[PDB]
Amino acid sequence: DPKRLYCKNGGFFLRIHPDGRVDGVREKSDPHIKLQLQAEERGVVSIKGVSANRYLAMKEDGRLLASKSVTDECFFFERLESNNYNTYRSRKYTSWYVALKRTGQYKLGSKTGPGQKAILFLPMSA
Amino acid sequence: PTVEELYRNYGILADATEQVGQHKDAYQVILDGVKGGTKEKRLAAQFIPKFFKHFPELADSAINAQLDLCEDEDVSIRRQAIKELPQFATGENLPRVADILTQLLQTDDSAEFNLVNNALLSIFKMDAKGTLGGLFSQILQGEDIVRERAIKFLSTKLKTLPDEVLTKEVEELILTESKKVLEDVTGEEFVLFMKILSGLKSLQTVSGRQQLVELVAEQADLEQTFNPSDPDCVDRLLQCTRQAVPLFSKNVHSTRFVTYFCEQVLPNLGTLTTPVEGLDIQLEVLKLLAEMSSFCGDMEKLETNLRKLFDKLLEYMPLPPPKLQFSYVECLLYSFHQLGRKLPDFLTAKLNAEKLKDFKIRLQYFARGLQVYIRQLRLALQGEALKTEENKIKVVALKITNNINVLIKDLFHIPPSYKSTVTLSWKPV
Image 1 (cartoon, chains in turn red, blue):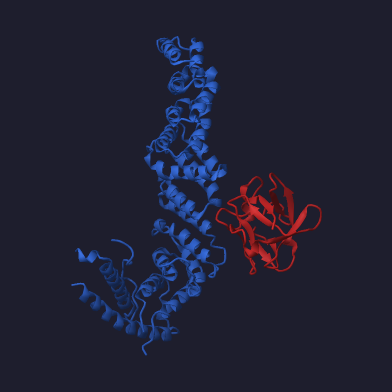
Image 2 (image 1 turned 60 degrees about the vertical axis):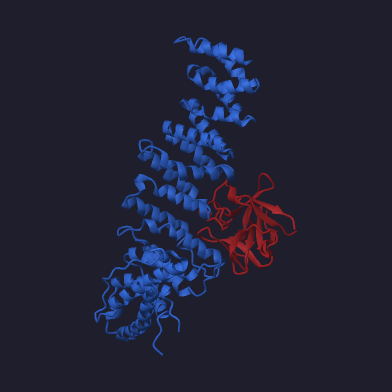
């Protein structure tokens, strides 16, 4: 089932562009916010942009890009929080979370931590 | 509890002289006044804070009694209680009062809103660090409405405090807390925090303004590669860079910004999109680069950036065989006149004899059509009619053409000179 990731910080939907950009948008019907959460090992998921055919990733300096192929940086720990909001922590860089800022851009992983409003994402239907 | 019993117990506590702490029963009757009606609560909002200093063993119950009055439905009851809140900020109670007052900033009653600001400024003079903790913790964690009002409070009411209050450690704490906020602010929030931080006395020095310049540099994310296709990528860089211009002096350099504009923005200036009507996105970039070029120091790749700036200038200075964009030339010719000082060999080298020969031909052909338009402007301008929107354009156009003509003559010395000084047209006297 395809889902949308609604960020608690500001209310942005996680968006993955065909060129590899990752950010947030408030429009409910953006074609690039339709995501597919593939389950890997127990507790680890992968986020794929449907309209972009790219997988969400976080590189060396905590920046979020969308590569066309699944790499080492495309696996994230999914932890369920309150309420129905989840946090996605990089499997390779185990201290940096996927996060969107109030401006809509991605938050640098080196400036993310547990208990932030920016790291909480809500899976939504449609 | 009625108004008769409250007035009688007020006299018991007032006429007690120095034997006040023993009439705890009389103060308890006043504390129970919050359970009464309108007239009973309007008296409790006055009497609870007046004798609060004489009963520390009832501090929690008294602060709670006043807090109930601060959340009463009647706005006149809240105004009576909020005004007397600084009386409770004694000892360990100030950070709790600071949190309540910061929470109360979201009121939309103009009379109540003023009383909350005066109470915040009151406990600010008492414990500046304690009040800031109550304000910044709501900016970092509270709702968006509280974060909005609290930022506006620092943006508008810090200038009203006496200089005795804003000590060095208070300004240090604000900068320490503001840098925690700047990691997640919007475009407008960053503009407010730059006014707050630059207003601090300890940050108005040469070293202080250099720290503020580094803050907007990390906010601009100058290591992020520039994308000319995104309309919001340009409007965010321009807005973030405009906050750095008022801080640049002869010893506070803009090299990190001039390097970014020359390396990544100038070679891609044609691909600039604007989603707002009546705004020339390319001229605003050139306007911003022209202001910064006056404070640029030793550059990383000086010759490469100078060539990229020189190539963009020749695009607007045609060879003699069209309309001339004097507004674009004023910004580009000024920036090259500023950065060209650092490398006169860019024109005065035997290898660059072809570039210098071609350049002086473009300057000479441009000056012919320029001086034609100068006296053509001064013909139409020969104190009240000058204030018309149709004539003010010719006034700034005369400043643009004069600045270009001064810079061309400075560069057309057989040894090209760079000592002329002009004032940009869109900058006042």
